[PDB]
Image 1: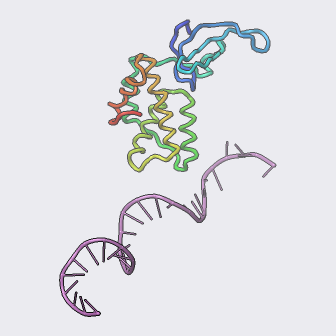
Image 2: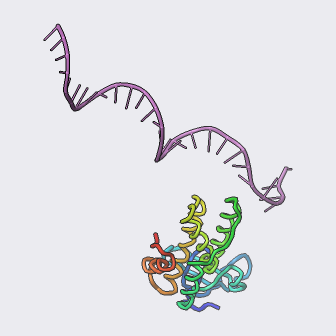
Image 3: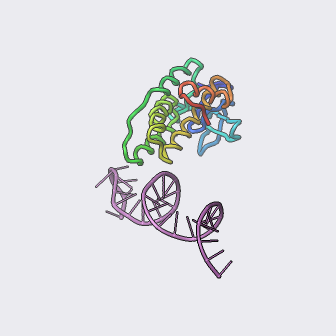
Length: 162
DNA sequence: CTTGACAAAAGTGTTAAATTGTGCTATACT
C-alpha cells in the first residue's frame, strides 16, 4: 500500500511522491487508482491499485541503502556481449527497468571500460542516463538536491560528476 | 654596372592528425 505522501518510484519517471487515491473511470467500472506526481516534470501518473508490484512501482531506497549501492557502484561489474547491439540493448532495458542495484551494478563495468579503451557513442548515453536515475534517487532518499546527490558518487568513482 | 653577405620567401621531405571509405552484426520479421 501507499499512503498520501509516500515517496515512491515509477519507471522511468525516477522518483515522485504519491498524492493519494481516486476512482478513475476507465472503460467500465472505475477501480481504485494510486496517484504519482513529479514536481520536476509537471507530469502526472495513474497507477492501478490492483497489482502495483507489476508496474515496477517500487519505493525510494532508505538512507541505509546508500553505502551498499555505492560499493556495488565502485567495484561491481558484469560481462556483456561484444557486438554493440545486444550490449546496448541489455543496458537500455536495465535502464528503463528501474532497478537501482542493477543500474549501479551496470555503472560499475561501464565505468571500468570508459576509462580504459573508451566508451562508444552509444554506451555513453547508456552510462549518462544510468547515472541520472541514481543521482536523482539519492536526492529523493537523502533529500539532497542533484548538486549534493551527485557530489556523493564522487567518492566511490574517483572523479566528479556532470 | 658588380661582389659578397643575408633574410625572407618558396621548396622539398617526412609526420602526426583528420577525414573518409567499408564490411558487418545471428530471435524473429517474407
